[PDB]
Length: 269
Image (cartoon, rainbow, N blue to C red):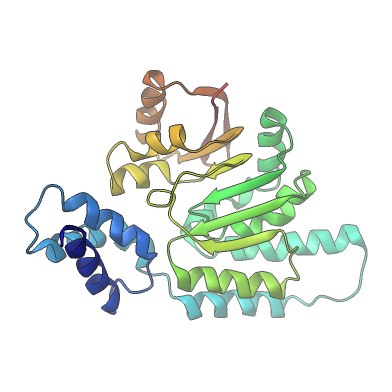
């Protein structure tokens, strides 16, 4: 009956309409972390308390059907008549660039996609695959990392299943390559996995906010040839990260500044 409270509390948080479409393992993790330091009773109050704070941010505002409506309108407005490879490739970028302009996460990076992956791959080399943690609308970035040379598999994941379903239905409308895969996941709660190139765009601070010292732990647990970690330029939090690396056994291979974001390319060698 020790692990029951954890499962009962999490099931009660999930069955309710508020924190419904939220990756269940994420709910279990918070619940399992708070159970070690707060009384079994009234845990449901404090788990919800931390969901309103750290997890309420990307869950609030994102409406699954609403997102798909805006994306599906953008695709039908601009027509897709027969043309040349080069021109259709520029059309594919035009639409994907508008889709990226929808949510805040990828709005500011649209100026950089034109050459973001080209610049990242100069350092890391062309990866055989990309894992994109907390992907948001970044899967619609395939036109750019594809011309940059990455024709392998892309596995993007985020917390909201409503968003991810909208992305999957949208990607099929664009006749996207079968290698552009989206699923739901949480790099914080899911088991540590392997990758070639791991992308953590605007996630390190959010991760430390959701759970202390988690971001650095994840970078040491996950196996990857290289990993890209993005931070905004609100002028603070970026210095805290490069300070965290001093103690770890990780290495900064390159530090790139594109648009209004600083990208750190980290490696185990």
